[PDB]
């Protein structure tokens, strides 16, 4: 049903304990506060589906949402693509509009409504903070800045179709008391970011009002770009190879179908099947899987205007001899080769990602998370250099 | 200024000679005939820019357009994606809506307003027609059917963004008296095709009226999808290799930029340049050109959510040893390999083509034209088997 | 059906009458073209390889014999055995199976006017090094190479098929049936795209 104790809170919400369910044992509650919760519930669900570790479970009512319990980091991370207001005042000379390409990440010391300054990434490390048991140093500070930039880009991309420019945003992290992971732990409403109208060009430039932002955010959870990956295999004995591609495609939310066809045996049939994927208007990418001399990829590519990846099921036995039938093609063939089965699915994702922000986001989160993972393995092996 | 003699004509236009300029020495002239000319002037310019050989030079006035002089083929080529009207009546059993995937191509004998029947592709060959010197047989009849299907698909694609479904179309060819090529030689207005509203679902299904079609056709000449190919080269000594890619990209209308960067020398710089192409929102595809051990492609792919093609400048000296640094990458890398410089540009085109119909069209026309070329070389060598 | 006389040329063209057709149809069940495939192996340790070829030949109704001979050890003997297959008038195709440096195929091909297929028993261990002794032959050698054991039998069949309609037919039915099989596997996997 619902319970609750006391606990902490921020400026927009009040965090409460939740007996009858420990861990995610947290409830955020807080006119227009219901708008602020609708926004923060989408951005979170969005960033979460993309792959970003974020403190959010399910939406709750109109002005609430439960999320895992965690100790907050007293720092305000801000990311910019364009310099405006405050920044200008702090950085004399930078004319408004200056675009930052990496883009710029700055963090502000303790949120304290007093002066709450700007800390150097080095003053945070020397701060030697520790929450939920996690001592915050190089590794952790590096994760948050990287994750902030990643979260920025994801939202920046997600907004573009609504014709909105993410100028800059503010975000706070927190260590999950259970998993001990640094997570995007606190609400993101219309005062967490700044969205130009981007159809330097419009009025004096006015951030979208929480009202307009409100009735658009749910649209970021869906994409206009449809996409499909069709896997063609010359022989069912490679079914396993094709399934790794299919499963991989599943990780990037891209629908994928497996099919059996032989350029060598049923030339005519291969073209036929090609036609029914071409004629139905769904943007498609073909992945050709043919062992030995691969004539499947070459033929497909030569008869379709869509991309064609040859992903040969090589084994070290004769692999070195077979790949060349996939590389070395007669002129006029765009056909590309990718040896890794999941790798080919990833490439396909990156192809569709150019049009589907939801896919792009998953690629981006993944890039980040892989870095997070690298970072941790090094710290774990570093322990053993004593 | 302008001249003219007599000559022939069709149902919508009257073809006139044009002294003061032989060859293209033709003028098509013909209330709402100005609409019919505006439509036929775009579809032609469109099909022409895509690469289809079509009898059209420039638009002329409101109700006219000059094009090269040519002898028409007395046949009406029709292509269908969906069965409706006439077809149903001729093919009992085929319920309305049946989708044809190759898709269906039928041709009707002599346009004669009498019965003007339906000819078999074999009755046309046996007809032994000959215009402008070109005896029409297997090869020529095969070209027209193929070109018809290609023209269909191009227009089918071009329309989709206006939320229109090309159900079927009618088209007539002609041998150019000068070049002797079979060309899409005659007007395509609103009575040349049938466009559903496609947002089986709407009203009884009503073809768009020449008025609405009129004020949309010019939009088919432009695309919503922006695209850019960025070529990264580890060394200026491969500049020539990169330029073949750039020039190739030029053939598919895709803007392309060359840049110098070394994963091995300026790791930091490569990431920086990557960021300024990522941050500016233009959908981009990266083509990595690095000789010897290629670490440029692998690094790029691992730090960007956009596609990355490795296109190594191999030479037979050590080529067999170098390609493997581009293939065989550590896990989590979608990076694809394409040896042919123009081939890599083509692949990039096919990637962008999934979103830019103008690019897709060029790919499609090219597929067709290459077939036309194959067809002719075989006929020319066939002459020498006497 | 309708059967012309084919010796546009004859009368107004008259289909054969059920009477004449009747006393001919049983002849379609037999062929004038005789055929034989002889498998030469340099070593009995490849007997298994040669048997896949023999069994395969059996699938196309072509008689096949296995024999042991070494170009390197019994040069003279190989030529002798070659002669007794040449001299008996049976149209023959030779399939040479020699591991390592294959000199059996090259020598056979150079001393017989009949076709000679080299079908090396390669293994991925040193296969990449051995095939080249079967490819890359001195000039004047028509010798062809086919890696697949059954594949070599098939090629032999297609050779004899040019003269034996019964063999041609089996090749054709097989082409069809393989397509039927492809078609069904795709439909069966298509079921699983729901």
Image (tube, coloured by chain):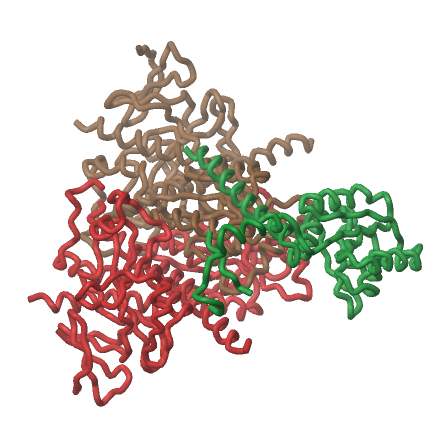
Chain colours: A brown, B red, C green
Percent across and percent down for residue C170 are 61, 48
Image quadrant holding the N terminus of chain B, namely bottom left
Residue under the point 22% across and 67% down: B111
In the displayed structure, A228 sits above or below C164; it is above
Residue B262 visible to the viewer: yes
Q: Nearer the viewer, residue A179 or B153?
A: B153
Instruction: Give me the residue at 42% from left, 62% from top.
Output: B367
Of all residues, the one furthest to the bottom in this rendering is: B20
Q: Residue furthest left?
A: B31
Q: Nearer the viewer, residue A98 or A164?
A: A164
Q: Looking at the image, is A229 positioned above or below residue B139?
A: above
Q: Quadrant of the C terminus of chain B?
A: bottom right
Q: Position of residue A55 (x, y in %)?
A: 39, 27
Residue B354 percent across, percent down from the top left: 38, 52
Q: Does B351 sit left or right of A168 as displayed? A: right
Q: From the viewer's perspective, tell me whether residue A116 is left or right of residue A208.
A: right
Q: Quadrant of residue C82?
A: bottom right
- The image quadrant of residue A25 is top left
Residue B270 image offset from top left, x and y in percent: 51, 56
Examine the rendering and report whether any part of residue A138 can be seen.
no
- On the rendered structure, is B168 left or right of A341? left
Residue at 84 percent across and 62 percent down: it is C107
């Amino acid at each position: 049903l619902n319970i609750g104790k006391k606990l902490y809170e921020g400026k927009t919400k009040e965090v409460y304990e939740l007996l009858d369910s420990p861990g995610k044992v947290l409830l955020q509650s807080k006119g227009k506060a219901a708008i602020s919760n609708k926004i923060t519930s989408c951005i979170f669900q969005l960033l979460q589906e993309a792959g970003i570790k974020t403190a959010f479970t399910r939406k709750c009512g109109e002005t609430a949402f439960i999320a895992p319990q965690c100790e907050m980091i007293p720092i305000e991370w801000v990311c910019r693509r364009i310099a405006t207001g405050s920044f200008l005042k702090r950085n004399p000379g930078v004319k408004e509009g200056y675009k930052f390409y990496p883009p710029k990440v700055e963090l502000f010391f303790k949120d304290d409504a007093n002066n709450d300054p700007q800390w150097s990434e080095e003053q945070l490390i020397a701060a030697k903070f520790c929450f939920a048991g996690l001592l915050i140093g190089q590794t952790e500070v590096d994760i948050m800045s990287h994750a902030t930039q990643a979260i920025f880009e994801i939202l920046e991309k997600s907004w573009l179709p609504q014709n909105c420019t993410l100028v800059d945003m503010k975000i706070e992290f927190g260590v999950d008391v259970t998993t001990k992971e640094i997570v995007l732990a606190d609400v993101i409403d219309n005062d967490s970011w700044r969205l130009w109208p981007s159809g330097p060009e419009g009025l004096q430039m006015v951030k979208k009002n929480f009202e307009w932002v409100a009735e658009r955010v749910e649209l970021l959870l869906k994409s206009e770009s449809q996409c499909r990956v069709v896997v063609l295999m010359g022989s069912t004995s490679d079914l396993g190879h094709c399934e790794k591609i299919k499963k991989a495609c599943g990780n990037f939310g891209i629908p994928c179908e497996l099919r059996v066809t032989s350029a060598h045996k049923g030339p005519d049939e291969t073209l036929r099947i090609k036609a029914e994927y071409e004629g139905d208007g769904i943007p498609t990418v073909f992945v050709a899987v043919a062992g030995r001399s691969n004539g499947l990829g070459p033929v497909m590519s030569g008869n379709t205007a869509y991309p064609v990846i040859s992903c040969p099921p090589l084994t070290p036995d004769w692999g070195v001899q077979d790949v060349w039938s996939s590389l070395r093609l007669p002129s006029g063939l765009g056909c590309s080769t990718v040896l890794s089965p999941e790798g080919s699915a990833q490439f396909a994702a990156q192809i569709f990602g150019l049009s589907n922000h939801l896919v792009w986001s998953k690629l981006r989160a993944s890039i980040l998370n892989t870095w997070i993972s690298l970072k941790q393995a090094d710290k774990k092996i570093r322990e053993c250099n004593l």
